[PDB]
Amino acid sequence: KLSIAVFALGSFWGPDAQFGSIKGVVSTRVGYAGGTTNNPSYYNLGDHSESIEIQYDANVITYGELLNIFWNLHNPVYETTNRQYMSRIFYLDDGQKSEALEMKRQIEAANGEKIYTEIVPLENFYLAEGYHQKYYLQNTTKLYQTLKAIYGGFGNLVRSTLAARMNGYIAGNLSIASLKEEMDLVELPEDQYEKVLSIVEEIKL
Image (cartoon, rainbow, N blue to C red; front, side, top):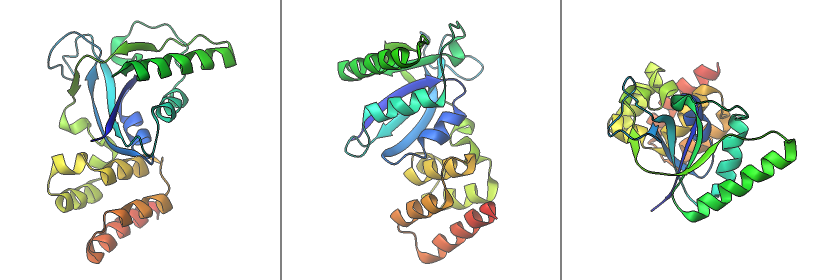
C-alpha cells in the first residue's frame, strides 16, 4: 500500500528520470491523463497530456515535497492550449488539492509570476507504450538487458525501484555513489552486483 501522485509537465522522459532519482519514490510509470478519450496512445492522444504516475512512500517523502520538485523541474508561467505538454496536477483527494493550491499561491506570491498549472481531479490514467518506460535505461542496452534478466522481464524491471534509480543515473540526475547505495538495498548475489557495478562504473568511466 503506497501513495500516488500524478503530474503533467511536458515530455515525460525527463520527469520519469528526475522523480525516479528521489528517495521515497518507490516506482514510476509514464502515461496519458487529463483527456476525455479511453485508451489513448502516443499517436492517438486525443486531449490527454503526457503524465507521470509516481508511487511514493508517504512515510519517507510528502506530497508537498513532490510538488516542490514538480515546480522546480519546469516553470509554467505561460498560458498555452497545447494539451499534450500542459502543466497539470491531477489530485486524488481534497488533501492533495488543498496542498497544490496553497503551494501554487505561495510560488506566485514569491515571484509575482502567474502560474498556469491546472489543478484538476484525476480521472483516468492510461499507461504509455513499453518503449517510453524508463526511456534512458531502456536505451542503454547492456545495462538494460542485464537488469531485465535479473528482474525476470520487462514488466518487473520497469515497476522496480532500482530501475527508476538507474534511469535517473543514466539521465544524470543521480550520483554513482547514491546509485551504489540503491544497489545495496536490493541485496543482489555478489556476482550480479559486481557485473552491474562494472557496467555502471564504466558509464561513469
